[PDB]
Image (cartoon, coloured by chain):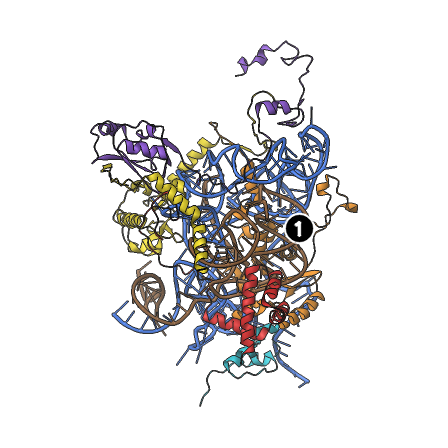
Chain colours: A cyan, B purple, C orange, D yellow, E red, F brown, G blue
RNA sequence: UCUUUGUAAAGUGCCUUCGAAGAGUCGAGUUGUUUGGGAAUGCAGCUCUAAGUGGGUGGUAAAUUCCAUCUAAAGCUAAAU
RNA sequence: UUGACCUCAAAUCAGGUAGGAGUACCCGCUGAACUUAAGCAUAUCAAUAAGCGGAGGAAAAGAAACCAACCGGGAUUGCCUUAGUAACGGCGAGUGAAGCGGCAAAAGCUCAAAUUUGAAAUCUGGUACCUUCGGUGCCCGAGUUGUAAUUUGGAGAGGGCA
């Protein structure tokens, strides 16, 4: 939610809606960064899941 | 060179061939074409008539290529063929081998008709021709067709 | 790629969202200094196409330059001369505000070359530019010879000489018949066509 | 400041031309330096011919389209038609132009023939091994001189038709001058039955 | 078209047999890619309409196309700029009116 | 010389899906300067501010309709000087 | 409470870098006036001198958003021509290019817009070793708001097929 500058992800909800992929505006880019072993991520996605 | 200029003959003559009364000054009449309408009117209107004014239309971005059209007269036309073979062409005047002359490759745009081409048939290649030039070419028995 | 969406979405400069962003951004650009380092570009897509790679060595300054014309500095507004030059107001500077921004940034951080600069925002009395700067003395940029041309000594202070995108525009260095006076430098062309070229064997 | 029957001499020296005068005393000196530069370049890149191979192309404008001249480079279409790749042609000493386009067959035929007779007249050393001892020629343009196309036979029979060539010229000119009005009038008749 | 083979006229020029060369990938810089049309469709949906654009929509849909076309020429650069914008807004009106 | 150097790269012919190509930017108006550039050459300020078979240019402003040629708003590069 | 991240600081922090000189030439900005017009205001001198800023052995420009209208040429630069011409100008004084052509020299390219997604494959810095204008190993960092490879429109990419 806290992407600075905000226009980087401003179109993602629109892009996600048109393609129909579920999207979640989660609080904190540091949380995304720490689940990708980085400082920040500003975005994260799953494309495949174990059975 | 200096030793022949008349200033050398003018050493010793006080006014240096420029008059005592006149006292040759630095710019008495102005500078350049100055006063072409006020005090040099007579000189301009006697020796350069038509100097002042706007006659004609303003042509924007005039390229001399568009108007490239060198003139060629019928009398000068025979000069294009090389000398060694000119003599055999004036003689044996025959329709079935008529010399062809690439006036355009020779650098001439139009064929003009100063006249008196002899009664031999000559194929003329040019960008443009005139009424009398083509008539005389036909009169000589030749033909003129256009190129580009 | 996100930058394709970012470029087109940043083109709509009068949309409600872009207006709100520039309303918020112009304020906090104003409450900061005239020249201040941006921690990251606020137009990453524009920086990317102007050559900004997010590797250490590249520097982004934000610079705030006054709008309006240039008032001729003559005391009491009296220019002593023919009336064709008495005009002290309404005189327009010949270098774009982009070019003025690049110069003041360059002279502030003299250890960096001005790669480029781009409009980022604008208000009544200021224009805002983010100036792409590249450090020529950083080993990262000295290496990677895709960028080692800028640490060549001929490229130092290219904004002062007028070599960036704005400098090329201001000097009118473009191909065409529109630029016949300014094709390689108007002073070179002027000197070219005002020389008297005399030869050993006169023509 | 003006008198007598003298032509109006438009001399552009109101400016301070004196600081900007350039007199070429070095014309002899620059010629010797240039010849030395040609000597050292040839000695540097021996035995390649010190210059590229230029195509023969027709000059533009109506004034000069009667003369062919050495253009910049062979268009990519000409290079492939010779059976090469653009990059390979550049290395072996063939000037290549990417922005020129081939729209004339006669020019195209000359250039691909120019390339074919260039390949058969050069030899290329292999990258690895003992390069054969070759003697350096200094002018590729001279070895393949630019040739004026042969127009037609010196003298042929008269193909008369009584066309009155001048009348054709007026007819063609009048049609060009009146093409619009003759079309527009035809348009008005067509729209108004 | 083939030339007429004479120094003046409509198709003045020497007779030559031509090539019709392989078209350059250039001359297609304005061609809209499939992804590019997708991107610009997305932007219009999410950014919305610019201020004057909404005024033009009001003007074209209430007063008349010609009176909106003149103000677009003033608002935008030139006539063809106004022509392309107005034809676009009739399409957007039709698209936004339908369904 | 090679255990350095081929879980190597490069070029090439088809057919197919494509083919992304730069925004306060072009451009327009006005102002000032400048140009040989003249209904405005270029630049600059302010206002307005785009499109994608689009855009620019085609030295008379405008509209209608075609054609021709390039691909801007990012960048580098020796020599002749 | 404790770790982050984001931004902003400080340090006689580690390592660097800028200034100033010269300035003949070069790149911009600013910019006059004397003078000429037999006066003078537009014009001219002049898009000059002075002032300011910035480099190099040259610099700049440079590979077309070109010139053309041709049977088309094909980065830039310079010379001869164009041409004292088209054009500008109290259309007065004066000002005034460019295309084509010949020649000198010729050299072409690189990014951004593509996902590597079967593995950030990238890079600085510290440290140890060495054969040190650097290389290797490990580590800390930067970097996913995008670093390498691949493509730059002349094309090119992907998918087979040999």
Depth order, front residue of A26/C154 = A26
- Left-right relation of C31 to C10: right
Chain ID at mark 1: C
Above or below G134: residue D167? above
Q: Residue furthest top?
A: B12
Q: Which residue is mark 1?
A: C93
x, y percentage for residue D92?
Answer: 32, 51
Q: Quadrant of residue G47?
A: top right
Above or below E30: residue D50? above
Depth order, front residue of D139/G42 = G42
x, y percentage for residue E25?
Answer: 41, 61
Q: Quadrant of residue B81?
A: top left
Q: Is residue C163 visible?
A: no
Q: Residue furthest bottom?
A: A51
Could you tell me which residue is drawn at 62 percent across and 60 percent down? E74
x, y percentage for residue D153?
Answer: 24, 39
């Amino acid at each position: 939610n806290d992407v600075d500058p905000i226009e980087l992800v401003v179109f993602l909800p629109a892009l996600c809606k048109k393609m129909g992929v579920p999207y979640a505006i989660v609080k904190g880019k540091a949380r995304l960064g720490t689940l990708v072993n980085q400082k920040t991520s500003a975005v994260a996605a799953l494309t495949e899941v174990r059975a | 060179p200096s030793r022949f200029t008349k200033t050398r003959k003018h050493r010793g003559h006080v006014s240096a061939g420029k008059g005592r009364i006149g006292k040759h000054r630095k710019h008495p009449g102005g500078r350049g074409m100055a006063g072409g309408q006020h005090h040099h009117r007579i000189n301009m209107d006697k020796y350069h008539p038509g100097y002042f004014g706007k006659v004609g239309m303003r042509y924007f971005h005039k390229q001399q290529a568009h108007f490239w059209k060198p003139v060629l007269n019928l009398d000068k036309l025979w000069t294009l063929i090389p000398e060694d073979k000119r003599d055999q062409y004036l003689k044996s005047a025959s329709k079935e081998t008529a010399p062809v002359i690439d006036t355009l490759a020779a650098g001439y745009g139009k064929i003009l008709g100063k006249g008196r081409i002899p009664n031999v048939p000559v194929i003329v290649k040019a960008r443009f021709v005139s009424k009398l030039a083509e008539e005389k070419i036909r009169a000589a028995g030749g033909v003129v067709e256009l190129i580009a | 790629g996100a930058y394709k969406y970012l470029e087109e979405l940043q083109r709509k400069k009068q949309s409600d969202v872009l207006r709100f962003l520039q309303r918020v951004r112009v304020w906090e650009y104003r409450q900061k200094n005239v020249i201040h380092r941006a921690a990251r570009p606020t137009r990453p897509d524009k920086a990317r196409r102007l050559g900004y790679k997010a590797k250490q060595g590249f520097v982004i300054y934000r610079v705030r330059v006054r709008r309006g014309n240039r008032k001729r500095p003559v005391p009491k507004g009296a220019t002593y001369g023919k009336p064709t030059n008495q005009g002290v107001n309404e005189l327009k500077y010949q270098r774009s505000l982009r070019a003025t921004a690049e110069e003041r940034v360059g002279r502030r951080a003299a250890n960096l070359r001005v790669l480029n600069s781009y409009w980022v925002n604008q208000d009544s009395t200021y224009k805002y530019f983010e100036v792409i700067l590249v450090d020529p003395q950083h080993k990262a940029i000295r290496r990677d010879a895709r960028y080692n041309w800028i640490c060549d000594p001929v490229h130092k202070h290219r904004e002062a000489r007028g070599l960036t995108a704005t400098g090329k525009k201001s000097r009118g260095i473009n191909k065409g018949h529109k630029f016949n006076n300014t094709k390689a430098g108007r002073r070179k062309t002027w000197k070219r066509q005002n020389t008297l070229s005399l030869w050993r064997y006169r023509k | 400041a003006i008198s007598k029957n003298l032509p109006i001499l438009k001399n552009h020296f109101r400016k301070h031309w004196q600081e900007r005068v350039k007199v070429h005393f070095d014309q002899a000196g620059k010629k010797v330096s240039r010849r030395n530069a040609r000597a050292t370049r040839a000695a540097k890149i021996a035995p390649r011919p010190l210059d590229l191979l230029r195509p023969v192309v027709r000059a533009p404008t109506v004034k000069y389209n009667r003369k062919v001249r050495a253009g910049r480079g062979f268009t990519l279409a000409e290079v492939k038609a010779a059976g090469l790749t653009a990059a390979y042609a550049r290395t072996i000493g063939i000037a290549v132009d990417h922005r020129r386009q081939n729209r004339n067959q006669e020019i195209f035929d000359a250039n691909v023939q120019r390339l074919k007779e260039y390949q058969s007249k050069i030899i290329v050393f292999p990258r690895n091994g003992k390069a054969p001892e070759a003697e350096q020629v200094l002018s590729a343009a001279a070895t393949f001189p630019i040739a004026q196309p042969a127009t037609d036979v010196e003298a042929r029979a008269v193909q008369d038709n009584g066309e009155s060539a001048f009348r054709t010229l007026r007819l063609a000119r009048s049609e060009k001058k009146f093409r619009g009005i003759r079309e527009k009038r035809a348009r008005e008749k067509a729209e108004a039955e | 078209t083939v030339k007429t083979g004479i120094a003046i006229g409509l198709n003045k020029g020497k007779k030559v047999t031509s090539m019709t060369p392989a078209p350059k990938i250039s001359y297609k810089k304005g061609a809209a890619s499939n992804r590019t049309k997708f991107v610009r469709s997305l932007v219009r949906e999410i950014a919305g309409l610019s201020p004057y654009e909404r005024r033009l929509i009001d003007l074209i849909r209430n007063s008349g196309e010609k009176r909106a076309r003149k103000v677009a020429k003033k608002r935008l650069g030139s006539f063809t700029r106004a022509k392309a914008k107005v034809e676009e807004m009739n399409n957007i009106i039709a698209a936004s009116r339908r369904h």
